[PDB]
Amino acid sequence: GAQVSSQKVGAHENSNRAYGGSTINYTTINYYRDSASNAASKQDFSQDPSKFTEPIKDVLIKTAPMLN
Amino acid sequence: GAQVSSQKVGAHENSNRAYGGSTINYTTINYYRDSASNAASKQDFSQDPSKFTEPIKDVLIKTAPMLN
Amino acid sequence: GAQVSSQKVGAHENSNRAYGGSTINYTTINYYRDSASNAASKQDFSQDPSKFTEPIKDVLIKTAPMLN
Amino acid sequence: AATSRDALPNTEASGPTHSKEIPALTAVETGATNPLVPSDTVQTRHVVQHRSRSESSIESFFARGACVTIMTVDNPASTTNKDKLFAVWKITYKDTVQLRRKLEFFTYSRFDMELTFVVTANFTETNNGHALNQVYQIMYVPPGAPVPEKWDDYTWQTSSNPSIFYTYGTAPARISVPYVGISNAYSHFYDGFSKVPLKDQSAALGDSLYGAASLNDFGILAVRVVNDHNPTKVTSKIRVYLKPKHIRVWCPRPPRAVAYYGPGVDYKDGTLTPLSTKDLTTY
Amino acid sequence: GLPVMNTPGSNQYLTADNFQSPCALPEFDVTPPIDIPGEVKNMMELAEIDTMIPFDLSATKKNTMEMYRVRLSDKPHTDDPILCLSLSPASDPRLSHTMLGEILNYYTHWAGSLKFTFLFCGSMMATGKLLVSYAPPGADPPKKRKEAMLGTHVIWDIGLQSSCTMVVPWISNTTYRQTIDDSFTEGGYISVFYQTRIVVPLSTPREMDILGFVSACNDFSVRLLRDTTHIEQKA
Amino acid sequence: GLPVMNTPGSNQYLTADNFQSPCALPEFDVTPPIDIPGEVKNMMELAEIDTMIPFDLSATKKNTMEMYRVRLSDKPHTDDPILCLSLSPASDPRLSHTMLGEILNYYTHWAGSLKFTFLFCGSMMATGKLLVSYAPPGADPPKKRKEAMLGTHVIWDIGLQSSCTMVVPWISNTTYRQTIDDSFTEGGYISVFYQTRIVVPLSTPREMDILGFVSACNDFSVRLLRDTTHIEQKA
Amino acid sequence: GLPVMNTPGSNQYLTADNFQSPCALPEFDVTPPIDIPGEVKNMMELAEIDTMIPFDLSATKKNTMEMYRVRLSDKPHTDDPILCLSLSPASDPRLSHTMLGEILNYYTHWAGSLKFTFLFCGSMMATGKLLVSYAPPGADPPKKRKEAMLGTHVIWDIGLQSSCTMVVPWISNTTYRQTIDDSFTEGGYISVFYQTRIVVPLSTPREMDILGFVSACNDFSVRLLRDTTHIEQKA
Amino acid sequence: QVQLQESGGGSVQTGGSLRLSCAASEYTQSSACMGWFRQAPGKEREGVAGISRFFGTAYYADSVKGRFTISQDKAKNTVYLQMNSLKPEDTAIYYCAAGQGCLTTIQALGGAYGYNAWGQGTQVTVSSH
Amino acid sequence: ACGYSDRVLQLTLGNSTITTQEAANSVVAYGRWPEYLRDSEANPVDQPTEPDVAACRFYTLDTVSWTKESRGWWWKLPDALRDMGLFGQNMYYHYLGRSGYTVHVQCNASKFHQGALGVFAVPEMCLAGDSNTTTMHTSYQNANPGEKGGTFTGTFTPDNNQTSPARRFCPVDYLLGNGTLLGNAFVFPHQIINLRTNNCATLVLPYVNSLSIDSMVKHNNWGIAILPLAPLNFASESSPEIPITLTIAPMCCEFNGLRNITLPRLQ
Ligand SMILES: CCCCCCCCCCCCCCCC(=O)O
């Protein structure tokens, strides 16, 4: 029941027959029954700030006049 | 001889490419020969309270008269 | 998600039905999400010293005259 | 499908222009922030961006534990006049400040709390007597359960209260607790009260604190030194650290600008001066 | 050995833990179980069983069989309540000692619907009508037939079918309520009133009593396990 | 048992750790979430929202509503700046308290583009033209229309479209900039000047104000989490 | 938990260890690398580059530019050496400070072939012939053209091709040699002599100098990492 | 910045004591040796005193040693400057000077070079009235 | 083509219609339109009360005056509608309830008048109190002024009457009465009534809480803050005045736990 995930490699070791290049992955294993016990996956998602930036009813075309 | 079970996810991490969504499971491995050594699975079952609530010989139809 | 690599055997145990001969490999498992946490693979690469030794614009033929 | 660690969009090449498309001019009164990029106002080059917002995701921003309280317990001599000290502390994020404000960037949040327990101990009386390694039991007393009155009463038996048995000199204690809120998310600001003062009721009978509710009552943490009375007194402090993992947030609020004053939003006199001096025409 | 690393929590003892451990008596021939009738699967099913409420807890009646009795009379109609009760199943004296409540005392949060059943134990020749009322909290606690009549209520006819059940539906602000006596998580008010009055013929006991029972509905749940305060050991 | 070996770091507590641990309340029925509008995914999206800049921070105006106001007049043209501002989003008083900056105070490195939007709040009968300027660092900080005009700048016409945005493009030596006030990682200078002058008819308020807002662009990022200094607890 | 057993070495800190450990700054957006010209893969390739040898290390010349110069003259032929040098790349003063040697100071064992290149820096009108000699150890260190002529040697003609390289082939008893000055692992002797003599016409500087360089060959290797002694901190 | 706000402009006679203080409450990479600079309108701006943020690295200008001392409050956060036995040659405008990253006042020891936040300026006159 | 503009708008809720010619579009808080309580999100069991047009229509509060010395103005929802026809009645008789609102503030001037007004909707607008002795000390009566709402001040005044404290709010304007710079107020859904451009601000607010439904009598979910960003000036006069008016309309109004009338002590 292992959870193997990828690592976005930053600094690279002069290696590509072990480290460096060829996709470096990590393993994770949940030991507890309760989700509250698990570690943070950190594999999150982004969104569009619109709901805060453009909370306007009518579509905003940046090139057009705001007021028309 | 691992025992992989599911976790009823409560709070969700803004994740679904690791945590959050895609069924999060846990692993368990019995290390001892005696059942008495094992941890509590907690994967239990419910029943119908009838044997305590309706221990009556004759079928109780809630919409009908109790006494008839 | 284990990483099994080879060992360049130096001293040999009078063994070849376990150790000594038949390719001895090792295992490695990444436990952390961040690449910065990983151990050094040590499986590196060499290059040609030319960029330091022969940083000359024109090809150096060792058998020919340097100046021609 | 855009993850937290994915690269932000590349900035593309753009040359000169002169027409009827107006990027620079808008109107903020509408409540919308103009979503411009550099190419809208200046001539730019083709640039393959590499940076990502990996480090600013809600998860990552709160991916740290913070000292929430500092508890004090001791183990004095048997001959003592004052009773052995046991600490009781109501579970809140609002005794400290740092963590609070972070939490306060938002109005509501959902998270599973991970708690750690760093324990310190020291001698207090200038003597040469000795003490034997201590064990500390941190019991969680939820609202409703009996809260200890003595270091040695029946409560510390813990039949259903979660309790930690920490031996001094070893790895600090750490547990996990799920989202335990009575609401669907933990509320950081409550615009209301608990009771409704009614006309045909005495004002006294109808009063309640502003912004106070059960939404935040999680009971208390009780701790003692399990060791029996020692000839030479020993003092100890348990520092608790809270990390809100697996976190979700709602409704952004401006951050606290004036130092806090109580668990509410109230502020005191002479603290209301956050900005220094700076003249309008100088860099 | 395999390179390992100690992370926080090591060596500690959390009483709520769940791990395996070495056995003290290996190969012990455990005695197989037999079908003992009446096994229970969960605490809530005990909760769904109707237990009798010690209503009148007056100085004289408390801690006596009489506390379970609610005396009724053939007095002319009045708009005054027969009994007032607060929706604090786990904290109000009258509810606190019923199985339901006692159970609730082992948890911190309570949610779902409840049912109040009343048993008329007067003579067959006795007749009457009543109004049992449940008012959600927030307003003036009912004290006269009038306001109570505005809330949730069952109007019960005394007859051949001896008992009547009023269901107090789950109406809450929060997803779960506190086992403690609290304002934010207040439950409301339960109240009984005379609709008509109790009527009996001659040669019939003019005053009688009523029994009351309370239990949980199939969708009642509790959470957050804690130690009760209705039990203690002195020294 | 399985032969194991303790490697450095064992038993330590790093607050930045991320591991699993035993649960204090097993089998707790967590309350499911509900769609609460306005959830945020990352700190930067708060950063992209335009917040008002407390420009004039004079002894008299600081810590008062007036610090947000930048007074303009119908005075004859002058080449003198209306307002001078340093590109130190996270460290210069005027920028330091805006959401953008406040956010920046939680990180150590900052990178990407920024945008300055200005709002004319004078009368409709008021007209004028201005030059908002951004000069990269390294030279004499602009103080006259002339030098500022040489850098990045938007020339804004006052009209029916109430606001104007100037984008300060990411022009840096380093890949990331310091949240501190520093020379090596200096950002440059922001400056506003009168292009023409403010013109109004008779029976029209001769002096007016302007509002300014700053936010991040879709390609703004921060790194290295640290504790802020705009908050503290004394004893 | 899984039954485990602590084996020797647990809890210790070996500086030469290589394990994983928890990160202090999770999710840090590392800045991608850029193609910086001149990256090095291994220490030996620095070793293969020719560095200038500070030959004459006399009281007067040591620690001065002059130590790199080896003065030659148009004196009539003599069988006396121009310069004597011991094959202790990592321990003999003259070799000890060249990159090659300095590098060698970080290791304990050294193996492989070496090359000595000499540069005539006299006038074009100057002519001459020399004999550069490498004698394996074990016999009388050469001091006259005669014995040196018996060993490995290149006879160099001074002309249009300004420099000459003599390769000291790997001739050793051991598989690897010691970075220290040692007899068992002795390397041999390097020596330069006049073959003819230096000849110049009139109106030509009668005395000139020569430069010498030493580097490793493609099959030179080192092992056993140790701290150097050519660097130190007092208190 | 840090906060740098200074005062203490008392025109004492030749041979009196004067105290100068500069606020440094906020804790940025805090004023290391700190810094005190005087500008004599006859000369120019020059460095004078300075004690390390944490350490006891206090440098003293040749002209002020012994008479002028530097000290601060590692809590109340303000930097004191005891200037006694004042000559008429010390009549100048003083300024406090934040030298951030302590190494700024470790490498060069004295301020001047590693100094980014500038003080306001207090006029001190030491005359024969 | 047909002349349709974002400045010219008309909204209709029930038997009430609002019309304007100088709008700056329209804001829908957090991009969420008001809605009825979903089955998947529900909690009280009883069948709910949906008054519809009865409660869900525009309601105009008491007009206030904008002058040079005004520091700001505030109102809470539902509070500010507590005594508005049916909605209020429906509020006082039910234990729980939820609702969204379309807030429309009105304030026109002349092309010769100037000033900017920040209309901010702050969910959970928990304001600050007036005492330096006791925290969270503001009484229910002073907390909920209802339709008249309250105001902000430019100077904090701590109540020193320890005998019979005032127990009210003392919301400083620049700290947006909550201890946070007004400057960031823009994080909340908002609009700006800048006289030049616009005469009104329209915001649509969905129901926001930590739970599906709550006791509106005990708790306010949204706050309405209006503060002059720029000062009010006209021509060259010394004391100009321009009225400001707020009309509010519940949306998707629903209530549960019907019972007897709630008679709170408002004074
Ligand atoms: C023995 C371990 C203790 C287990 C019980 C922990 C009690 C749960 C308390 C969690 C809530 C803490 C308050 C902070 C939440 C918030 O920011 O609103």
Image (tube, coloured by chain):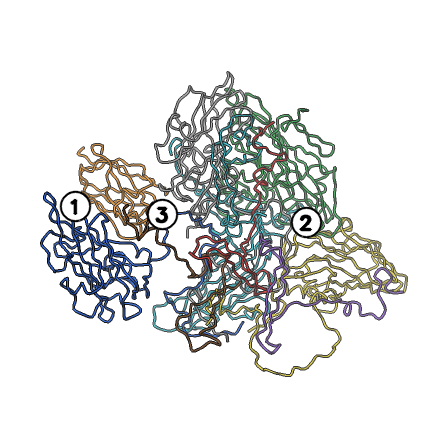
Chain colours: A red, B purple, C brown, D cyan, E yellow, G blue, H orange, I green
Q: Can you tell which of label 3 and label 1 is closer to the viewer?
A: 1
**In the rendering, which numbered label is found on residue E138?**
2
Tell me which residue sits at (21%, 46%) in the image: H60
Q: Which residue is mark 1?
A: G123
Residue B22: x and y in percent read: 62, 56
Look at the image and tell me in which quarter the C terminus of chain H lies. top left
Q: Amino acid at mark 1?
A: Ser
Q: Secondary structure at mark 3?
A: loop
The answer to which of E141 and I16 lies nearer the viewer is I16
Disc 1, ligand 1: is the CB inside 8 Å?
Answer: no
Disc 2, ligand 1: is the CB inside 8 Å?
Answer: no
Q: Amino acid at mark 3?
A: Gln
Q: Chain of mark 1?
A: G
Instruction: Bin the neighbour count of mark 2 within 10 Å (Cα to Cα): few under 14, some 14-19, many 20 and up.
Output: many
Q: Are marks 3 and 1 on the same chain?
A: no
**Residue D210 seen from this side:** no
Q: Secondary structure at mark 1?
A: loop
